[PDB]
Amino acid sequence: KLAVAVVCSSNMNRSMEAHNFLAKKGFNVRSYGTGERVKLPGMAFDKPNVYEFGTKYEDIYRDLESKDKEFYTQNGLLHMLDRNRRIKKCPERFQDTKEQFDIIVTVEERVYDLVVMHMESMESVDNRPVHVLNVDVVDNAEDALMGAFVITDMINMMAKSTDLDNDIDELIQEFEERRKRVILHSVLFY
């Protein structure tokens, strides 16, 4: 019943996986990235595949396939892109998006800093609150859904709350103790 957004850095792995779960659960959710360019793993640790933040996931899939068709279907990148084409049209940049939410769950500290850093950029008349919650999650694809699970278990809990803004500060305190995690939470204005 609330607007949610998950944010990793390339809106490829983590963010999408949480995006899937939160959606198949019924939650109103969007997913973005903060990076400059979508970047995926390549043949080396120093040789990746970088793309425009506007390219179709469909084309990125076409691209990889018309290259190391084998390699990429194996490590997962092709199936992953397969899971994404069926939800969103193509990866989006958080920074540039008129869309607005109540809860913005980032997936890495590094990003948490960008989402906030940019939230403090403009300032509108709306003046209604949005909570930026960080829930660390390894960029790895295996942990991706392992994080979604955590990520949804927390929003699901926060979901059912007649007055989020007040007790949300305590729900986090409880979620922190139940999952033995460190949920960075900061206050930004829309």
Image (cartoon, helix red, strand yellow):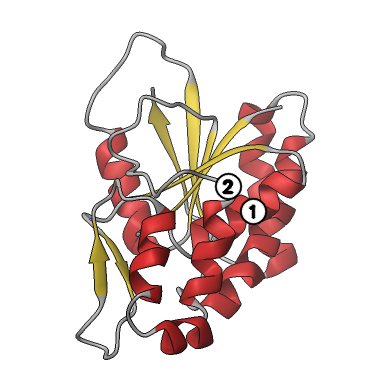
For this rendering, which residue is in front, 55 or 190? 55
Residue 127 image label: none
Specify whether 189 is left or right of 164. Answer: left
Q: Is residue 83 above or below residue 76?
A: above
Q: Secondary structure at mark 2?
A: loop
Per the image, the residue denoted by label 2 is: 87
Q: Residue furthest top?
A: 125
Q: Quadrant of the C terminus?
A: top left
Q: Is residue 11 visible?
A: no
Per the image, the residue denoted by label 1 is: 20
Q: Secondary structure at mark 1?
A: helix
Mark closer to the observer (2, 1):
2
Which residue corresponds to the image point at 70% horizontal and 38% vertical from the top-left? 27
| Residue 38, image x, y percentages | 30, 60
Number of other residues with Cα within 10 Å of mark 1, as a class: few under 14, some 14 to 19, many 20 or more: many
For this rendering, which residue is in front, 183 or 160? 160
| Residue 176, image x, y percentages | 65, 60
Q: Is residue 188 visible?
A: yes
Specify whether 141 is left or right of 92. Answer: right
For this rendering, which residue is in front, 107 or 70? 70
| Residue 7, image x, y percentages | 44, 51
Which residue corresponds to the image point at 77% horizontal and 24% vertical from the top-left? 162
Residue flagged by tag 1: what amino acid is it?
Answer: Asn
Measured in 3D between alpha carbons, the distance from the residue under mark 2 to the one under mark 1, in whole angstroms, is 8 Å
Which residue corresponds to the image point at 50% horizontal and 37% vertical from the top-left? 131
Is tag 2's residue or tag 1's residue first in the polypeptide sequence?
Answer: 1
Q: Are marks 2 and 1 in contact (CB under 8 Å)?
A: yes
The quadrant holding residue 121 is: top left
Q: Residue furthest front?
A: 66
